Length: 145
Image 1 (cartoon, rainbow, N blue to C red):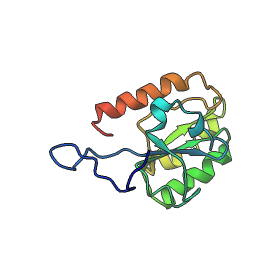
Image 2: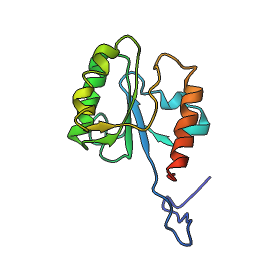
Image 3: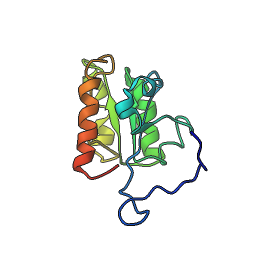
């Protein structure tokens, strides 16, 4: 398929379009997570370019798929230093919640981060099939694309 790179795809009378919700989903470990997201939803998300820093301001939301405390911390940081209070999504691991959803409080309670997505267990590839549904559907309820 060939294109002119810049191409006019309209909607809403002219080329207006609804606000695009760009969810850059990433993790340190789960970098190939996008590459294991079903094609159905895969189009909605994005991979990093301005790696682990400057690609966070660029997106509607940034997700953090992590499995460990300090994996989250490093990225959770970046969210506020390059944006502050974005719709960010944690894909997390159970048990660790006593530290993981607590160190996050210091950002969450301070409104330095917010979310619209119901967090799932990173090691639970099973729930990704229902997780992504309600990401899609929810964003449909917001009227975003």
